[PDB]
Amino acid sequence: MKRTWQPNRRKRAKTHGFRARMRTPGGRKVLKRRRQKGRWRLTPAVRK
Amino acid sequence: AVKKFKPYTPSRRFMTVADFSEITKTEPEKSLVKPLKKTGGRNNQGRITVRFRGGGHKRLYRIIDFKRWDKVGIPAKVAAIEYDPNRSARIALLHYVDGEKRYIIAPDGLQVGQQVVAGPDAPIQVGNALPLRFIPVGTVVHAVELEPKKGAKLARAAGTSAQIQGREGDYVILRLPSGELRKVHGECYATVGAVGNADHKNIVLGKAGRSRWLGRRPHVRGAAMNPVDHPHGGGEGRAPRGRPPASPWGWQTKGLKTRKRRKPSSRFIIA
RNA sequence: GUGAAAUGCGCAGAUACCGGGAGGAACGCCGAUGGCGAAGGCAGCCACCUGGUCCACCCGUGACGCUGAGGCGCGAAAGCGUG
RNA sequence: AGCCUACGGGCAGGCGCCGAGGGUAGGGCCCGUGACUGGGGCGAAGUCGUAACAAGGUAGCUGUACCGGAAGGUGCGGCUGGA
RNA sequence: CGCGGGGUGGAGCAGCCUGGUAGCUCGUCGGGCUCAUAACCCGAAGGUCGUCGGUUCAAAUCCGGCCCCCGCAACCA
RNA sequence: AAUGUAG
RNA sequence: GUGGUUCGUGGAGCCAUGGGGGAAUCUGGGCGGACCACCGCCUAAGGCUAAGUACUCCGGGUGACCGAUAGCGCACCAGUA
RNA sequence: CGAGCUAGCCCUGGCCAGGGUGAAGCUGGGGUGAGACCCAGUGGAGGCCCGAACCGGUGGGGGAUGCAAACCCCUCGGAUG
RNA sequence: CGAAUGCCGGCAUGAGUAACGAUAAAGAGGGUGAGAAUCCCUCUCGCCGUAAGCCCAAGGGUUCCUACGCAAUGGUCGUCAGCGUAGGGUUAGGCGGGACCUAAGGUGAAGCCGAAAGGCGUAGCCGAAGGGCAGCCGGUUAAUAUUCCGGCCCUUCCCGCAGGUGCGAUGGGGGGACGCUCUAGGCUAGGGGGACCGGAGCCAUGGACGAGCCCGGCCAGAAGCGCAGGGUGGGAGGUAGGCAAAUCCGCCUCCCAACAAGCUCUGCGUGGUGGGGAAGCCCGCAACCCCCCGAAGCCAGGGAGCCAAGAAAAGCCUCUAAGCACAACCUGCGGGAACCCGUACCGCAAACCGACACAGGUGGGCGGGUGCAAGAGCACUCAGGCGCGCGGGAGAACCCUCGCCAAGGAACUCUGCAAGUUGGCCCCGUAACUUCGGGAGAAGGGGUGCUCCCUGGGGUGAUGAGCCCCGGGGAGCCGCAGUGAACAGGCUCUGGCGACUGUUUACCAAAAACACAGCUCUCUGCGAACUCGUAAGAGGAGGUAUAGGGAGCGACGCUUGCCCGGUGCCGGAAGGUCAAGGGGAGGGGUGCAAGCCCCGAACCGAAGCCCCGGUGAACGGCGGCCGUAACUAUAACGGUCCUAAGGUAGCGAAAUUCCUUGUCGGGUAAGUUCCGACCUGCACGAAAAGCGUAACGACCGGAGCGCUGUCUCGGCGAGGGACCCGGUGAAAUUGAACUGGCCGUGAAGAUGCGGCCUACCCGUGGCAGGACGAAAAGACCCCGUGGAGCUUUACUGCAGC
RNA sequence: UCGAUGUCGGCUCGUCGCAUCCUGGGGCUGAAGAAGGUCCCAAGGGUUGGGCUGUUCGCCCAUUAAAGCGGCACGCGAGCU
């Protein structure tokens, strides 16, 4: 039966993207936080 | 005339449809002026703000003329009566001598081939449009502006009319389809006659789909919800409001007047 | 308003009077112990469509008539359905 | 396969069609009867009123409609078998 | 059982929170009106205030006790 | 401004 | 009508101001805790000003600080798997 | 931070084996003063019927540290809206 | 540190136990290698075949191919692998996306709004599975191919040439361009037959040298031809319009032309050419034609009907503007130029989502053949692909899934739960009741195979011959049985509820719940009311009273009484009260005073509320005690007290009745249920509707008939487990244990105290009485000045008005 | 006993008590016989099939020698319902 997760790359990029964080203030801070944490990945990476 | 059906199915027993004598000999609408795609959309910036709207046949919009004083003095022939999905009345496509074409909300009596015209000059007969001053006190008349040059606001529901009741300076007394009595400015245009397709009131929808075809979603009663949901909501098994009937929002809905008290629209109204 | 009353309306300005407007129903006098219609029934004025009837002229058809089970239509008021 | 034979045939026997009726199922008409129920008829001296007959004390009857303990009332129209 | 209300002439009800006067309608009796009976008129009669105590100078009334009549409550399990 | 037992 | 001050409408000044009304130029004007009168303090409605003060990404010095279940989450390729 | 589950709406696409029933309208005849109507023949309507795909989840059994954090079997509802 | 259901770690117990993940199924002979049930090959056996086969999207991201490997992973094994190591592999102007278009929506010049962050928003830009658009068939690799190669064929830019023309947009117009259902005639895909053509071979086992048997009889293809379609009037003059700029569109006016031809555009066929090409022996002979059926695909923008009335923009045509006409377009033809990104492999799954090589979920297309009326259904089967990554034995109990059963037939049970019966098609034949469509598959019945004879239509041809397609009548044959297997309704009578098809508690409730067509009340006159929002803004609605918001009842039929005193809502230019404010009689504090500062009564002061009235499909309500008839009973009738007024019609022991299994009747041998009645209705009743109602229902009750392993009452059988062997090997739980019975005792329910009795040590297959057995710091209950959801005439506030 | 002692009835399986419903003894009798009544001794063995209700129980049908009453956590859900 259909589970929560249904990978779709368009979705993922439009939603958790670098460009998508940066437009909102709230998102800008996400990035700020993760940089400052040292995360190797600021964004959910996605590609083909 | 209202077609009634034989009961080869329940529901198709109560259902009745329109005659289409009305309109005949013209269905595909006028690619030219007629169409802008119409935007289905049952609310504003996110949130639904009219409950129970949605679904229903995809629909194209006919762009009608509600300000006829552009074409003063130019007559036009009535070229066809056609179907409009977007309102209760039918519409007439008329070719102006001008070349130019437009759709008028088709008044009663109006028939293909007639010539029709708008101005202070115009003959006092069907479909012609005129300032209210140059229209004889007593005639019925529809598609009435409310302020001059603002477009026709009154009397456009299928089978509606207003009646000229009296004069009074620059202003002119009007009995509205409601029963209200309102002064309207003399320069406010109006088209002689009433609206027609007046059987429209008598369609018997017939079943609950159809209601859906017209994009009307089911409407759930107040009590029928729970208290979070509604004032009437709640009560162990079935309930009697519990004083006094109210919208979801809470404000009273049996008898409470809502129009704004100090409106400058006042002084113009009298019923 | 009645038999006399009372309910009721009215100093928040009624009734009585005047002017301006809205709306619906019914048509005074003429009008009669009158007329028309098979009946039920039909009444202000105008125009249009249309039924029956009467008189006169002795012209035409030449018994082509009377009645009518059943059928078919009309049928006051009240009442019913939709608006 | 039998029995007869005047070898052709005959008889017995066997099969079929129909068939009294029996069976299964579904209908139609009539008769009897039923907790209860609706009025109807009748029954020397029961309760409540007084509708009708005298302008019967609201002329009366009438078709309908609504209402009412009951006669009955009231609306709409009609009749005179009232004036 | 658990709460609350009632008991007054023959019937239906006042009077009791605010002790000292038992009032009202119907009915009953006697007399009118009628040929007579209702209807109507005149004038009367009739109550131990369910009941035994307590308080008070004085109890239908305030305070308890028994006797009747009616009303609610009897839930979580 | 009601109603008047049977024969 | 409110805020700030220790001040919570208090006898409630002072400082600031959303609204209304609305001056004067030293006889000008604010203040000294309602308000009057003396006595005194100061010159609003323009602006700039180091230093002495805070903090520790970073460099260094110390420790009656820890010593790998401690010390930073991480002594180890960890903000990883 | 989430509507890559779920609920609604919007834009644009795709899907519904094959059976059955046979509305209206036509045509024809009959009918009448004209009509109404009745008859065949044609026609092909419907939140129509049976029933796959597809959607579902009625009843029973099974499973119950499961094949499964809702599954399997038989049975059952819708199936042009 | 010994306890915190403590925290991290390690190691026990259950235990060699349960399990090893679909009951589609295996067997043998050969290879290989240290080692083989598990790898390779062969042959037999079984399973899938609208697939479990083939191809595409998404997702995954090297899983692809080859060579080495076998520690770990693989539920066993492993020589194998999607595992480890290494090396290889993805080729495009035409496929798909981008240097084209717009949709919802996003963004956003201007513009607007917001304390900041930010919110809106016109043009424009972004945004696709929608529009537009140029490639087919073969051959090659170990692994890519419409991408490489071969053959044939196209498109766009730039340049030159020739010839044509008033050329020329960011502008105007046309077009692009549209729904559902039903369908015509042509094709094609695809399929069947052929006695015809081409083929290795074959005659077994009694017969067959046969019109035998087996295999195969194609595909792509420009121009031009055909054959079907689809689109389209052609003039000449006026010209108020297309934000006049037009020779174009639009609109008048009139010669011709016409259910045509023509001009034009697709499909299909044919076509120069190119390719393919079976069954067969150790890997190898070169037909390609005739008939039939035939699309849901093509011609396509085809036709008919119907209402609910069915995208946009570019490309493309055409019109004119500045301009420019030594430009510039248009049409040929030649030569040049032609980027970026993807292209392996999996892809209903062991490679995707489900922590797993998980019995679960996943969109699109192809999906052969025969038979059963049809079909994508059902049985077998082609191509192709699989036997589901632990086996080998036994032949208990018991469980699962299945088959059968004497006689009886619901006696089972809360309940026919479950299982049976019934089942397709053809033909007879079908009741009450009905809204009249229906109730109808009502019920009930008969037939069904095969051989031979005779016969009627239809399609294709051609009117004839075959090849299909529907039939009609007759004789006859075999079984227990002809829808011979598989798919495949049990029916009836009568209540309650809901009119109806529908919707819901994802994951215990599918219903009498919600929805619903329809009925009523109410608001709203348009910058509508109402909703979202601080605003700007937007929905409502590009609607306008026959329309929009709110509320209730919920098809239809027949109906919906009385009470406006209380509460709401509506109306009441008077009155009463009423805040700030106005007004200042009078009073006070200070100054020598001019003054400056306080209070402060009359009275003028909204809304609201008081007051007067209306209002029931507005919140709501709809009585008590006595007495009375010529038998008794009861009370048509009377008295009286209270209320705002005292329940009408119609229902009534009901989904509502406590007493209750009320009482009568029906039904049965027997009926606390059921059905029909009667009422003293504890406690029905009219739009939170009243009473009915055809039809509908996976809704709840009550009867029959049929039939049955439900039962009397159980028996036997099949398979998968359970048991034995070999391979791997968990779990909760666990203070420690050397863990018997009874009577007592004990915190009052003892293996563990007392007395007595009983008992050699240790396993295995079974059962579930006990260990107050396990799991979860009880849901019930109370407690806490614990929380949270909901309510209101609790309080106090706020939004709003 | 609330860091859980599943909580009616049914089925299945029983086992016990006697205050005995049958069956075996027996004494009184208002015991003629037959059949009762009543008490005494005695559970060894028995103690039915249905309709109605979830029912326990009860009433009813047809039988019977009889159609007993109790306890076992209102015995028995790690046995089922």
Image (cartoon, coloured by chain):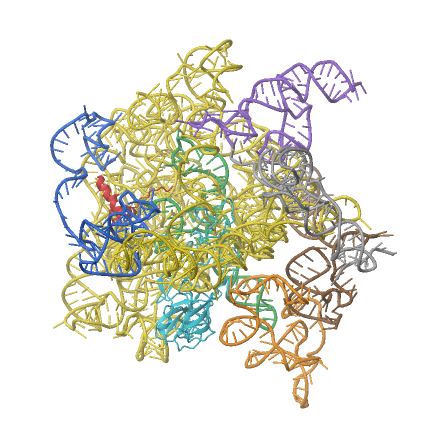
Chain colours: A red, B cyan, C orange, D brown, G blue, H green, I yellow, J purple
**Of residues H73 and I497, which is closer to you in this image?**
I497
How many marks do you count on the picture?
0
Residue I551: x and y in percent read 48, 53
**Of residues C55 and I149, which is closer to you in this image?**
C55
Residue I360: x and y in percent read 39, 40
**Of residues I513 and I73, which is closer to you in this image?**
I513
**Residue ID at (44%, 51%):** B248
- The quadrant the C terminus of chain A occupies is top left
**Of residues I384 and B98, which is closer to you in this image?**
B98
Residue D16: x and y in percent read 64, 45
Left or right: residue B184 versus residue I652 is left
Displayed quadrant of residue I74: top left
- The quadrant the N terminus of chain A occupies is top left
Please, is residue I34 above or below residue H52 in the view?
A: above
Please, is residue I181 above or below residue I66 in the view?
A: below
Residue I168: x and y in percent read 21, 68
Please, is residue I199 above or below residue I135 in the view?
A: above
Left or right: residue B254 versus residue A17 is right
Please, is residue H2 above or below residue B124 in the view?
A: above
Left or right: residue I592 versus residue D31 is left
| Residue B73 seen | yes
